[PDB]
Amino acid sequence: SMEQVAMELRLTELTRLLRSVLDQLQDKDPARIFAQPVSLKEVPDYLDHIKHPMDFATMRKRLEAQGYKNLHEFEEDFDLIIDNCMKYNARDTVFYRAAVRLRDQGGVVLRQARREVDSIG
Ligand code: NA
């Protein structure tokens, strides 16, 4: 139907908006601490600590497969990246500190993304 196509036009626009948002979030991690999943060869016990691992490349695969239905689902994944890091790593580590910074700097981008999604449907 014609309906499903206009929906597919919107999802595709949502995917286009979320891609730009993603690139802006990832620019706030110049050290690329969150770029890739935590290695299970290098941290074998990780899943005993963190039940839902998340990273920017894993978010990207989901994104290009048009797997985010709305901004809220996208935000949940970004928040996992941050919260996982803040549980697994202690407060006096470069990792924890990089997540605090990503959170604070990401807030501005997510603020405007919310307005842009509502504004343009
Ligand atoms: Na902790």
Image (cartoon, rainbow, N blue to C red):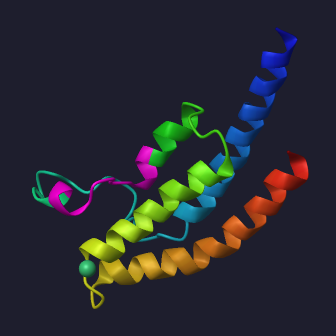
Which quadrant is the C terminus positioned in?
A: top right
Image point (34%, 80%), residue name: 96
Image point (31%, 83%), residue name: 94
Residue 52: x, y in percent? 33, 53
Is residue 81 shown in magenta? no
Query: Which contiguous range is marked in magenta?
Result: 47-58
Answer with the quarter of the image where residue 7 lies: top right
| Vertical position of residue 86 compared to residue 50: above or below | below
Does the image show residue 33? no
Residue 26: x, y in percent? 52, 62
Image point (43%, 61%), residue name: 80
Residue 78: x, y in percent? 51, 60
- Residue furthest to the top in view is 1
Which quadrant is the N terminus positioned in?
A: top right
- Residue furthest to the bottom in view is 92
Q: Is residue 110 left or right of residue 6?
A: left
| Vertical position of residue 32 compared to residue 11: above or below | below
Number of numbered labels in the structure image = 0
- Residue sitting nearer the eye, 27 or 44: 44
Is residue 49 shown in magenta? yes
- Tell me the quadrant of ligand 1: bottom left
Image point (88%, 48%), residue name: 120
Answer with the quarter of the image where residue 75 lies: bottom right
